[PDB]
Image 1 (cartoon, rainbow over the protein chains, first blue to last red):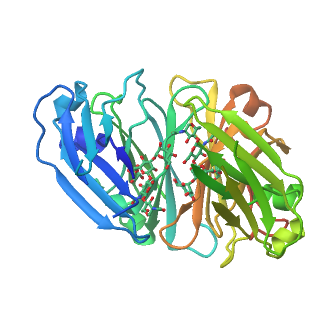
Image 2 (cartoon, each protein chain N blue to C red):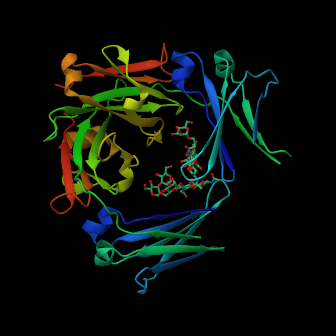
Length: 203
Length: 197
Ligand SMILES: *[C@@H]1O[C@H](CO)[C@@H](O[C@@H]2O[C@H](CO)[C@@H](O[C@@H]3O[C@H](CO[C@H]4O[C@H](CO)[C@@H](O)[C@H](O)[C@@H]4O)[C@@H](O)[C@H](O[C@H]4O[C@H](CO)[C@@H](O)[C@H](O)[C@@H]4O)[C@@H]3O)[C@H](O)[C@H]2NC(C)=O)[C@H](O)[C@H]1NC(C)=O
Ligand SMILES: *[C@@H]1O[C@H](CO)[C@@H](O[C@@H]2O[C@H](CO)[C@@H](O[C@@H]3O[C@H](CO[C@H]4O[C@H](CO)[C@@H](O)[C@H](O)[C@@H]4O)[C@@H](O)[C@H](O[C@H]4O[C@H](CO)[C@@H](O)[C@H](O)[C@@H]4O)[C@@H]3O)[C@H](O)[C@H]2NC(C)=O)[C@H](O)[C@H]1NC(C)=O
């Protein structure tokens, strides 16, 4: 029975402007989740989700909407996990410390033998702080569904700053409609709109 | 009290030809090896260190025979204060496709460049990534590699990152990204060079 409490994605916080936090309870034995704010102020209604897993574990998640300004101005949120009558407290707040905007480099790999129809696009995003980042790919100025790319977890560079890589597979028809895809990073330290974007062309 | 058992790195298995397997225990603890075939195991090395978060990490590294491992032996690590087992991966094989590239100079950092490597479409997941400069292997701490992730279709991919300084590429603009993998032919290595400028 462990619990995990996430921060809002940069995308939800700065672009969609409706941030949420999630409390995730992996219950090894088939539970109330209670939200509160350190400031003492009221919390919104939360959404409780539960599901038996493919290994027989019960998973419970509660998703709480939070105010944008509240979150950016340093509010702490608390998830309390209890049974009918000991408890587990998780809390989350924005990260402190120095800020640094991400640097974005997008690349297209050449044709590998035997797959004339598919190209791989890659994006290196590095030297940002703190490590919360959202990565999106755009094609023809429209944002692609999140499930079409995968992004690695942030790792520490040698000095300061984190880096992630993102991967996008494109078909021949996509780059032949227009040969410009965009890798966009959403991060709190990027100015002035909290986004940094770079284009790449297949041929 | 978590326990993990790791297969040999392809580098140790196919290049060095001295593969090891590692039993990692996080949070005295007895760590005992056995072979499924019943044969004896070699002498292992127990490492113990306290971490910053007050937990104690115990690892045991066990040398294994190369032919034994490649022909399908199953090894077991049992923990005593709970067992884990490991064996060569089975299934379809596919060689890694390697692409190495250099980032353009980022405004401000004129003395540094980032080399990166994409390696994808390989099966199974075990892979070793190394960087060479002027045909000499760089120390492993110079680079970092992501964990193998499943592709949308068939295969896995990893990314590797190597920061280099101005003096390095000016004296030779030949860096090589080399993958060691069981399905790569020949000699289980595939590699691709990149130049900065
Ligand atoms: C039965 O099967 C279920 C389903 O697979 C297992 O549930 C998984 O349990 C593990 C840990 O017990 C969970 O891993 C943890 O996930 C946390 C949340 O990650 C999600 O959300 C973030 C956004 O905040 C995404 O980036 C991420 O990709 C996930 O979507 C992480 O925060 C945790 O990381 C911390 O712990 C790890 C060690 O595990 C450290 O290495 C990290 O540094 C970090 O401190 C952690 O990774 C996993 O999410 C669960 N899967 C679910 C809910 O689908 C059961 O464990 C399994 N039961 C048994 C007995 O095997
Ligand atoms: C106090 O601080 C210490 C030091 O950071 C923590 O120790 C870590 O504990 C976690 C426990 O979850 C360990 O995480 C596990 O490590 C396994 C070892 O992997 C080795 O091989 C890989 C190659 O792939 C290396 O990259 C890696 O660094 C190791 O050398 C992983 O195999 C485990 O992976 C599991 O989850 C992933 C996805 O999340 C799956 O793909 C795997 O199949 C597997 O299910 C896992 O990541 C971590 O290695 C420990 N580090 C050290 C240095 O000891 C303590 O946990 C921490 N204490 C507390 C209470 O937080």
